[PDB]
Image (tube, rainbow, N blue to C red):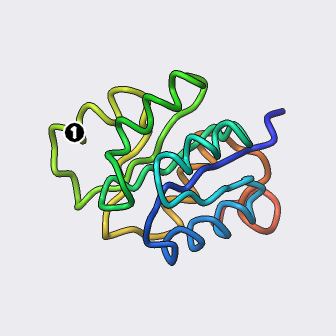
Amino acid sequence: MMNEKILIVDDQYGIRILLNEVFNKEGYQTFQAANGLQALDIVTKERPDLVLLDMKIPGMDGIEILKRMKVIDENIRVIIMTAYGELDMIQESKELGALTAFAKPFDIDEIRDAVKKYLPLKSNLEHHHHHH
């Protein structure tokens, strides 16, 4: 199976290592990038399947970053982060290969839950059971 890999493009390295460890723990080889170049490096270094492109402020729109990682790997997908769906770029984001546009209101679990249900390795903590 796929070894389950992630790329977190967030400048708020708090949220970034937050997401990092969260998915990482499920099995996700998550690599934290604060910028799209970092991200380019990350894709080229690990080849993540799920790249959380924080379109907020890190450096560039997760779209332009998702497509550059799409050109190096259209195998890849992106979980671009938004100010709760500012549309336009948001539409095109998911449209180009972003699975989800997660915002300020995040359950944390819904994001890790999402990554598993999109590409599942091990996930959770204790087997695959009804409770998360």
Residue 117: percent from left, percent from top: 60, 44
Work out which quarter of the rendered image holds the C terminus and state it. Answer: bottom right
Label tally? 1
Residue reaching furthest to the bottom: 14
Left/right placement of residue 84 relative to residue 94 reads: left
Left/right placement of residue 86 relative to residue 15 reads: left
Residue 43: percent from left, percent from top: 64, 39
Q: Is mark 1 on a helix, strand or loop?
A: helix
x 48%, y 40%: residue: 78
In this picture, is 58 found above or below 65?
Answer: below
Observer-nearest of 45 and 104: 45
x 32%, y 45%: residue: 61
Mark 1 residue type: Met
x 39%, y 48%: residue: 80
Left/right placement of residue 56 relative to residue 20 reads: left
In this picture, is 3 found above or below 12?
Answer: above
Q: Residues within 10 Å of mark 1 (few under 14, many from 20)?
A: some
Which residue matches tag 1?
A: 89
Work out which quarter of the rendered image holds the N terminus and state it. Answer: top right
Q: Quadrant of residue 120?
A: top right
Observer-nearest of 72 and 107: 72
Q: In which quarter of the image is residue 11?
A: bottom left
Observer-nearest of 70 and 3: 70
Residue 48: percent from left, percent from top: 66, 41
Residue 92: percent from left, percent from top: 26, 31
Observer-nearest of 55 and 34: 34
